[PDB]
Image (cartoon, coloured by chain):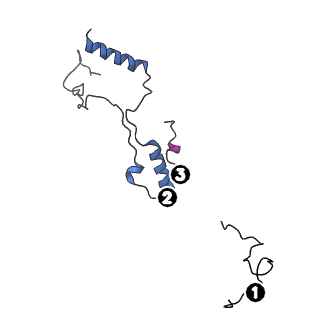
Amino acid sequence: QEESVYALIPQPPAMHTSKFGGKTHPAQFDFGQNKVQPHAT
Amino acid sequence: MDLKQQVKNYTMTIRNTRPPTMIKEQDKSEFSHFRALQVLANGDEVPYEATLRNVIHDGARQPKLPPRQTQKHPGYIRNESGGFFT
């Protein structure tokens, strides 16, 4: 309504990976055993 | 004057008290039309009727009778003394 025929038609990332990151291995942990074997038990 | 005309006059009085706001007597999908046009500007896939918008006005009654021409050919009739009509 405002005589704006120019305004009539409008014409116009990887997350990251931490350094600490790592899978827990059965070492550096005093709660459990300290080996990994195929079919021991 | 009578019941029907008094009801008529009261309604007309209401019409005059209210501002007509130069209204268009029909409202179509305003923001939907704007949104569809913006979708067309970039996405380049909009339904045709979604792009469309329709606005009506009163115009007038009296459905375009052809003109009467209000005037003959300036070779037949003359004013009072020789002289065209205007």
Q: Residue A35 carries which label?
A: 1
Kindly identify which chain the residue marked by label 2 belongs to: B
Three-letter code, disc 1: Lys
Which quadrant of the view contains residue B22?
A: top left
Q: Nearer the viewer, residue B48 or B68?
A: B48
Q: Residue at x 50, y 37 (%)?
A: A3
Which chain did the renderer colour green? Answer: A
Magenta segment? A1-15
Instruction: Tell me which numbered mark, 1 or 3, is placed earlier along the sequence.
Output: 3
Predominant secondary structure in magenta?
loop
Of badges 1 and 2, nearer the viewer stands 1
Q: Residue A11 carries which label?
A: 3
Q: Name the residue under label 2.
A: B43
Q: Which of B72 and A3 is in front in this view?
A: A3
Q: Nearer the viewer, residue B64 or A23?
A: A23
Residue lying furthest bottom in this view?
A39
Residue B56, image x, y percentages: 36, 36
Kindly identify which chain the residue marked by label 3 belongs to: A
Q: In which quarter of the image is the C terminus of chain B?
A: top left
Residue B17, image x, y percentages: 43, 18
Three-letter code, disc 3: Gln
Residue B84, image x, y percentages: 26, 22
Q: How crowded is mark 1: few (under 14 residues within 10 Å), some or many (20 or more)?
A: few
Q: Residue at x 34, y 18 (%)?
A: B11
Q: Report the Cα–Cα distance between label 3 and label 2.
A: 12 Å
